Amino acid sequence: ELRVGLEESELWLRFKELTNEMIVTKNGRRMFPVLKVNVSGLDPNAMYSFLLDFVAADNHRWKYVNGEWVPGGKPEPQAPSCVYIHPDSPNFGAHWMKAPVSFSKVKLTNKLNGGGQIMLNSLHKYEPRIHIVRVGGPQRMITSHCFPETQFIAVTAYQNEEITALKIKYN
Ligand SMILES: O=C(c1c(F)cccc1F)N1CCCC1
Image (cartoon, rainbow, N blue to C red; front, top):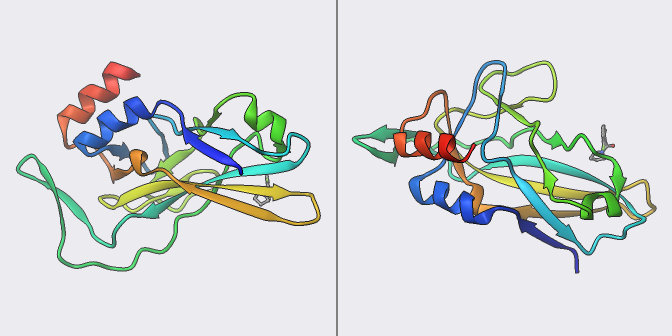
């Protein structure tokens, strides 16, 4: 049984208890914290690609009203985000299991852009998700895993200064 764990869940939970926010820019902004995943139970000799996408956790637009995030009343369906390929992909199971898989180079944007960057909708709430894709072998296989601890709202600037302070304290 293939096992997926969040590295530094301690710290993600402090962000989650405040409602986490991630900046999006036209050119794209790297994440803090960085999603880092512990993986065991891969075939060390099998080939795999690690993919990252962002599920829209609800269908609403959120707004920071009198020190509190509150959802809009007008849900619209949210099309899936594009997928980010971990740049170590494709690689042997041994490679992925020798250290936490760190998505340090993904950039979050608000604008449809050349390559790499993932476009999110500002003021929507997102739940990061990975796919582990067994490649090159005969039988293709996908294992997916969500990380509720890593939920955030996409923002063009921070609203809750408690988030601002935590971001700086721990970076
Ligand atoms: O063949 C690829 C791929 C890659 F793994 C790295 C660069 C470009 C690619 F199309 N993948 C299999 C499904 C998910 C990623």
